[PDB]
């Protein structure tokens, strides 16, 4: 006898991550760089939910 | 006897990630670079839910 | 005796990812580059849900 | 005795990905480049759900 | 006899992370660099919930 | 200027495995049952290297 | 200028494993049952290197 | 200028394991049952290196 | 200028393990049951290196 | 200028373990049960190095 049961909104589970010998050089001038986005949820009832964004200027 | 049961909105599960010897050089001037987006959900009731976006200018 | 049961909206599950020795050089000037988009869901009730987008200018 | 049961809207499952020794050089000036789009679903009740888009200008 | 039960809004669980010998040089002048985003949720009832964002200027 | 270089003897690499909802009942009396053999190498300089073997009697 | 370089004897690497909702009943009387063999190497200079073996009797 | 370099004998690396809701009943009388063998190497210079073995009797 | 360098004998590294809601009933009478073998190496210069073995009798 | 350098014999490193809500009932009469073997190495210069073994009788 349920009403609104076992709900799941914006969920992540069961994540396993391994990284041995990654080399990662980066060089930038006046930009916007993004790496390394792992295992992120969110909720946004009124708004823009952005992840991994980059605008060199406005 | 359910009402709105076992719902799943915006979900990820059962993720396994391995990365041994990736080399990744990057060079940029006035741009917008994005890598490494792994295992991300979200919800957005009113708005633009963007992931991995890049605008050099506006 | 169900009402709206076992629903699944915007779902990903059962993902396995391996990457041994990928070399990836990138060079950019005033652009918008995107790689590495893995295992992402979302929901968007009112809005533009964009993934892996790139506009050099506006 | 079901009403709206075992529904699946915008789903992906059972994905396996391997990548050994891919070399990938990229060079760009004032463009919009996209690679690496893997295993992404979404829902969009009112809006344009775009994936892997690129507009050099507007 | 439930009313609004077992709800989960903006959740992450079951995360395991390993990193052996990653070298990561970074060089920047007047930009905005982001790496190392792991295992973060949030909720946002009225506002823009952004993660891993970078704007060289405004 | 190599002598015996980049050798690989008895190797496996780049394996990805997914298994969603497999049911597997087994019943046995005085036998020898084997399932679930995944991603195994070995070397054997002097001997019988057997994998997934079953002898009800001797 | 190498002598016996980059050798690899009995190796496994780059393994990713997912298992969601496997049911597995087993029943046995006087047998020998084996499941769940994942990601195992070995070396054996003098002997029988066996994996996943089952002999009801001898 | 190497002599016996970068050797690897009996190795495993880069393993990621996920298991959500596996049910596993087992029943046995006078047998030998084995499950759950994950990520094991070994070396054996003089002897029988066995893994996941089961002999109801001898 | 090496002599016997960077050797690795019987090694495991880069292991990540997740287990959410596994139910596991077991029942036995006069047997030998084994589960849960994770991330174990060994060396054995003179002898039988066995892992996950079960003999109901001898 | 090395002699027997960077050696590694019987090693484990980089282990991460999570376990949320595992139920595990066990019942036994005159047997030998083993679970929960995680992250164990050893060396054995003269002898049998056994892990996770079970003999109901001898």
Image (tube, coloured by chain):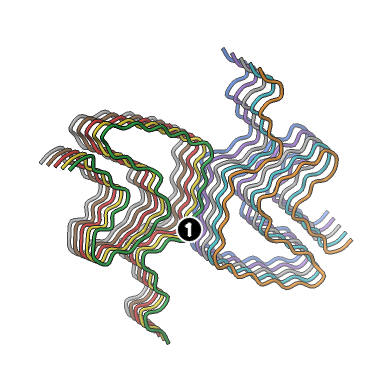
Chain colours: A yellow, B red, C brown, E green, F blue, G purple, I cyan, J orange
Q: Residue at x 54, y 57 (%)?
A: I18
Of residues C6 and B47, which is closer to you in this image? B47
In this picture, is F53 found above or below A33? below
Quadrant assignment, res G32:
bottom right
Q: Residue at x 75, y 64 (%)?
A: J33
Q: In the image, residue J44 lies at what x, y percent?
A: 80, 41
Quadrant, the C terminus of chain E: top left
Q: In the image, residue B31 lies at what x, y percent?
A: 23, 35
Residue marked by disc 1: A14
Of residues F57 and E17, which is closer to you in this image? E17
**In the shown orientation, is residue E5 left or right of residue C50?**
right
Q: Residue at x 37, y 80 (%)?
A: E4
**In the shown orientation, is residue E22 left or right of residue I54?**
left
Quadrant assignment, res J34:
bottom right
**In the shown orientation, is residue J8 left or right of residue E50?**
right
Q: Chain of mark 1?
A: A
**In the shown orientation, is residue I7 left or right of residue J57?**
left
Q: Secondary structure at mark 1?
A: strand
In this picture, is F17 found above or below G30? above
Quadrant, the N terminus of chain E: bottom left
Q: How many marks?
A: 1
Q: Is disc 1 surrounded by few (<14), some (14 to 19) or many (20+) residues within 10 Å?
A: many
Q: In the image, residue G25 lies at what x, y percent?
A: 62, 68
Q: Residue at x 35, y 31 (%)?
A: E27
Q: In the image, residue B36 lies at what x, y percent?
A: 37, 43
In this picture, is A7 found above or below F46? below
Of residues A25 and F2, which is closer to you in this image? A25
């Amino acid at each position: 006898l349920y009403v609104g049961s076992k709900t799941k909104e914006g969920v992540v589970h069961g994540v396993a991550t391994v990284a041995e010998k990654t080399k990662e050089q980066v060089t930038n001038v006046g930009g916007a760089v993004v790496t390394g986005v792992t295992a992120v949820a969110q909720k946004t009832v009124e708004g823009a939910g952005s992840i991994a964004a980059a605008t060199g200027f406005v």
